[PDB]
Amino acid sequence: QPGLAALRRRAREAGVPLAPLPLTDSFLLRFLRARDFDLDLAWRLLKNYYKWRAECPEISADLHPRSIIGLLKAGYHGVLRSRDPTGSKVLIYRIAHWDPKVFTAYDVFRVSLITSELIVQEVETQRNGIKAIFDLEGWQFSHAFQITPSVAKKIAAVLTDSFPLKVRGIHLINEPVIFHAVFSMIKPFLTEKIKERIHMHGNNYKQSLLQHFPDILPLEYGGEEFSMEDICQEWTNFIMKSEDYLSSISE
Ligand SMILES: Cc1c(C)c2c(c(C)c1O)CC[C@@](C)(CCC[C@H](C)CCC[C@H](C)CCCC(C)C)O2
Image 1 (cartoon, rainbow, N blue to C red):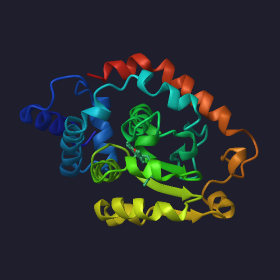
Image 2: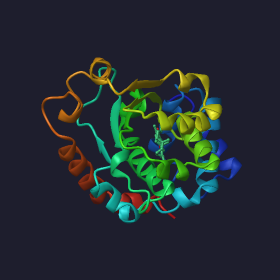
Image 3: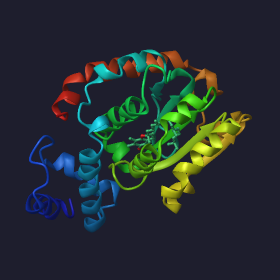
């Protein structure tokens, strides 16, 4: 593929972390595909990926699911079986199922990093990106307390140029008034392209959400074929089964 050997050589010359994550063709292609084979942009992304991991060890060091298995079992997250019409993988996060008295913002962030490291293995997802739906129903001030300026900047970094996944859309639904101050904290760090891709649906989201995700949503959101619990169980099992791959990319 165009630029693969050049990207490997740069990484080697720059002395990027020896291991884990050998510089296989499959690994490097994630970076080239995320940036449409633009070598310089792929290289910037690769360096940023390593930078972010080194700067956020609380989240990145151990990707084994044992630290967040309770959060998965609580029903916080699921991945749809089907892709959207543009081929993006679709992720669902439910704030009401995150108990901030038990899990920190770092733990919750780790869930997304685990899912992201798993789904990036799919070439269709490297090509078509992802969309994430956050159901903010139940957002509390106790969740907001966990979103410090540091965490806000880390969120903005992975959405923009620190992880090899194209964020094609972020859909916030059921956002309560009190969430505005939290989003305002993240906003200053986002690129214009990402801000343009964050949709605020509000409390009457059904029609608008279905327009973006026809025929693939769970029953809870207007879908008609399966439930959120079905997808949360299916994804949690897959994460559990992937514990050793996650171990191999852990440190
Ligand atoms: C690679 C990748 C990661 C790692 C990722 C996300 C996406 C789309 C990615 O492609 C979205 C979620 C996020 C940024 C982790 C968020 C963790 C926090 C603690 C969740 C609750 C608070 C948020 C204020 C809720 C809305 C977030 C959106 C503005 C993304 O992690």
